[PDB]
Image 1: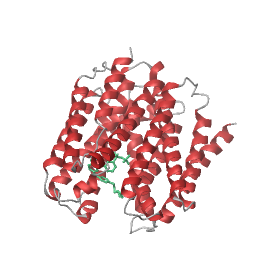
Image 2 (image 1 turned 135 degrees about the horizontal axis):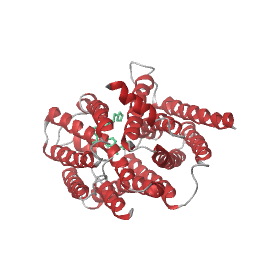
Image 3 (image 1 turned 90 degrees about the vertical axis):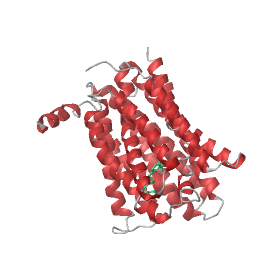
Length: 387
Ligand SMILES: Cc1cnc(Nc2ccc(OCCN3CCCC3)cc2)nc1Nc1cccc(S(=O)(=O)NC(C)(C)C)c1
């Protein structure tokens, strides 16, 4: 039944995201072992991830369905071993740009990871599995963060051994990906015409329109929420309080994702109302983050925002999967992720890039809340227009 592929994919997505080195990547990179600097990390290393993410998304979303979703998952596994082997034994900027290239491979193939299970189970489970998948990944993340925040503070574990544990985790995920069951088989304008037949599905260009625009703002909030927290209450101890909050904000999101899989609720006839309710919830949380000068209220707002967004994106992925009616599971997921990344890049050029408006983080989250309020009102007025 659905149990075996779902369990194997959940194990892969757990051990491939249970990465203790993620919260402490910068202290690892800028430190006594790697010996990098904050200039070479944010200007010569980090943008390589974005560039590699866009271009590797290009073949990822074109060719994933054709190769039946397993080799890209296996390619993600091999990229995990290469990325962390180079992180473990890499020196100089040149090697870390290769690390960023392979992490772009990993992040692009996450799209294949999310679509493989849809390619392998019956549509009747497409809801349950959906939540489970998202849930375990988020769970993995918080576990990793916890296994970080515990170890470094209760075993004096150097970041080198954190990355060793991370490599051990992602290598076992490679073995789990090796055991994934293989899904069964089945000019330029023609492809586009097929795309025209793929995005014409019922309520799938609408959920796609939410996915393309909402997750761009979500990634912007993810990137700059740490800066907002540092601006709100600049303290030397916040390093142990920021990530932990995210460790309890991702976990809550996991629960929200687990809400989609577990409960049996007809989403087809209620997905629009849930979409508008949780979109205005995201907007209200983001305005709650910006307006209140209290770090605890801001933490609660971030938790609410992350949980509601994770619930909404789980619903979006499930609703796209059921309504797709074509095998191009990763084509829609990949194109949605690529468009979301393009929108996020354009917005980060406009709002925070020094060549644009150069808005500080005080107004950064006001702009993000306004962006999400526009998303909600566009989607809320659509429901009224239909009725
Ligand atoms: C293991 C690893 C390898 N290479 C990188 N390169 C990289 C590091 C930071 C990046 O963010 C872009 C720059 N922004 C960072 C903050 C302000 C600007 C983009 C790419 N990051 C890595 N870790 C990492 C850094 C940020 C987010 C994540 S995540 O997968 O867990 N995604 C989040 C949910 C945390 C947003 C993981």
